[PDB]
Image (cartoon, rainbow, N blue to C red; front, side, top):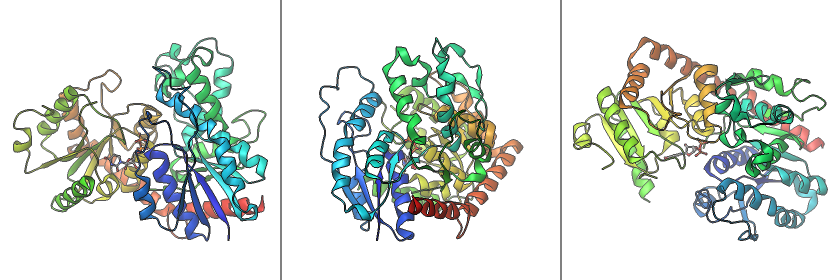
Length: 453
Ligand SMILES: O=c1ccn([C@@H]2O[C@H](COP(=O)(O)OP(=O)(O)O)[C@@H](O)[C@H]2O)c(=O)[nH]1
């Protein structure tokens, strides 16, 4: 009876899909231990998932928190929190190796690492254990990451010099250079975060294979590119397996309020607004959204974080028969699949994008950071299941644009065709997940390959 070791990167978007991956391993007769490397206590992702609650919810998974590593020396004023996180994660590889040596060797099936824990491949390599990266982003994003070394090698300036000039990667929709992850727009030699982030992320292909949280029919060109010898000249990439979509007190009350209210709304009527595990609009922006939402006349369910006075006077009273505003953390997956939900105003994180795709809900795209601006292009231009919200790169989206785009998705003929394409993709997501469907077949091919290694 073998044990898979799951070793996620920090953050809701890395841990939540890994828990779902764990359930797949369990369904296939593996034991699971999920090894948790906590970031620095100053990380916005520090204990953002309540692991005590997660363990209680999944008693068949063994959860193991690694002993802490020193980092105060690195925690200098002004350091980008993600640079500190990348450095801290490299420092955990000693504790990870001590833990892995504590497990009877013959019982180890594989090591599956998050996409910012890739240096742990050296630990599995040394122990003779197959290592896989769990890539929690799109397959197109993986295809970009694989091709970024070649793009950056000849350069004497950062990609910021290109402005909105399109970047072209094999298998990937063109997207403006400015929409690349922002930190990668600096010259690698000029910015430690750029160099470190590229050096870490690029190693997702240095193991035995990659488990991607996507379904092949959503991203067929990107999956083809990853198997194409030109993708990374002079290199054969390991196997890529599309195994998704893998979708997973005060919050308990909020969830109850949300779903009971949605149950009383007409089908496809509600605009849901929810912006990631940690994005927050300014107070001024929240007011602007509220005015556009009210003006649109549509029903809405709006998850609001306190900025990091919110609404016009009387906004809540006037909208009480068509809208519900809740605080801070909403049951997003259950809202998205609710038949009353008709649109999703999103920050375009990949889990959120997959959740909406799998539910058949068209998107109003408001990307903030990470690869969210890339996801926005993939959703609006590649997939065609969302719309842009003008001003998203400028620091303020006007109430006129909020109303215009809510009405476009919810009332216009263009919106109806958009919804129809979203429903088609939902159907494909469901096909991917059916018994003996593509994502089970892919997971089975991964299990065969890992056993044979
Ligand atoms: O109020 C909220 C905000 C976020 N989420 C979940 O938080 C995840 C966010 O992950 P994503 O990759 O979209 O973006 P990130 O937070 O990493 O930027 C998703 O699974 C959402 O369903 C949620 O359930 N309720």
